[PDB]
Length: 340
Figure 1 (cartoon, rainbow, N blue to C red):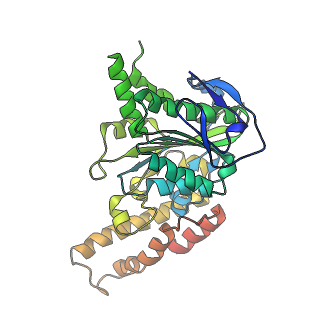
Figure 2: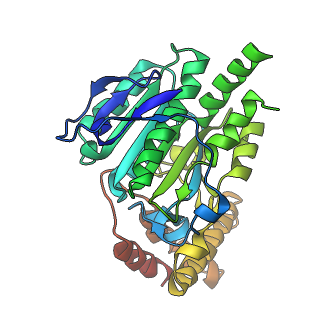
Figure 3: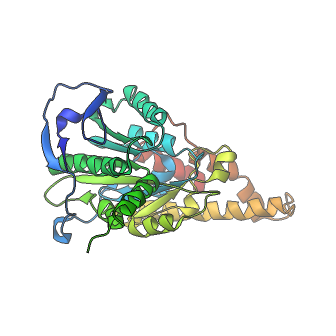
């Protein structure tokens, strides 16, 4: 019902009972305080408008899907689509004060992979990991999400710019379903929208910008749950199995992805360039079909040939080594080159 919070958790791995069970870093701050794991969301009047970009260092996101401080963004992917590597990039190449990761996963190996990632991360001294494995009870799996969120809420009240990751909402929701069945005004199912409303920028405080993962099954298809979360969140990033099998990483399909706060967090010249780039992406997808139909013949259509010769520079812009991060200025310089 209550959990540890505070700067003393930075570098720690926390289990569903809210106890530190491992460490991927040690810091000289030992602050440990206690807070309830369930808290009402902010009043509308306590929230600030999302108006400042949350930069990710990822070219396709910062140019076409720009996130804002306080936003909730869904990450939708099938099992082999690089969800975890994307999450690692979002941590490594963004600029948050503090990162809180809640893993509502399956095997301990997955957890251990994240711990060893964090052990070697530049961000290790500013991260907290909360986990629940498949072996823990459904109650414990749900609580891991609340604990992670409550830890983030403390850092927000202190004025920090916090990034929160919940992987995955899907396994959170399935645990919630089991907890509900154990019980049969309040439904155990309402714990999903009350969880998702907790992030945001506060007028009196800092912010929580939150990324929630959703699994797609079989083939990039949208669960009823996928549909419900999509409607609650402020946007979604879709990782395409097709793009991944083509070797494009990150496998973000920007034409099927959206940030709802985009026009609110970037300026006009950015808006113009992104719109132009999206039109070019659309033209490339049309040409790709024509090529598959065997109807593309060089020299027959000058506009088609011009689009053909842009495919390479566009793919190069979208593609990104997971170890590399780009500044906003760099990203906008690069996208300008591609549309020219």
